[PDB]
Image (cartoon, rainbow over all chains, first blue to last red; front, side):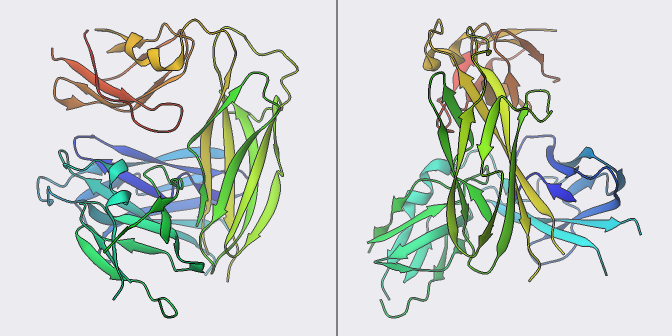
Length: 189
Length: 189
């Protein structure tokens, strides 16, 4: 069937557009593909445009969605902002195919670079995770002792609690290309 | 979701196999994982074999894909060759799009005229912007700026040119063998 080429899209301020690949490997099927953008509050938002908003995909094919910054200077410049790309495929015939993927808008000139963000996570046994960076960080493979903990996403300058059945802390993050990083030992307070 | 352990795989001539880590980080999801290799023109190619080509992941799992040289000694020996490893994760309903992770596989012959770390600094820029790469390596150029206008990311094939649609100083970064960003380099038109 249909596939998307990414699990997240980073939009670096200054870029005129970013692309998202949409593919169909089946020569015999046809789809209508509709897409739109929502803010983090769950509403349709016009600060980013995606085009074409509706297209037909007939057979084995690769199509590209373009995402354009129409923000017009109205975004926080000191942290990332989170949007959601919604794509829906309607087969040519309740049977629609729907995905939502993160769109992270990243302002120019943040002082901590993306690759140094993960190693700044602070853990407090009370565990509370604190993120003193301007990035949204996706934490996975989180372990405290021999116990495997749940995945979490920590917002810029935010805190999240991870339940543990009571009480070394290690983990990986998902990077900008959707890959797993190397294992990291957290900063424990 | 499903995440790969790397964004690119270097296959050094003579190695019998290279491994690629594939992981499902979510205990609530299940997947079928289908993988194949393409050449640089985007057509399925059998000079490299990936196995298993089809497998399933139920819950939190880590698997290893093996990539095997079946080139039969017919690769060019004076330049890298580019292949595309495609890993498609198809989600089981418990409704959603499959996700295809496409990463670069760079076959690298022994005896190249310059080691990898010297390549980035040889790139040549001509007003026409044309990027000319006189080295035996594929160069992945990011953070490309002409003066103060951000340009699109690009990849320059070994001994090839590429045109980037746009005075000012030209600055850029490249992605190295480990998927990391090099330091900014100053080019001159």
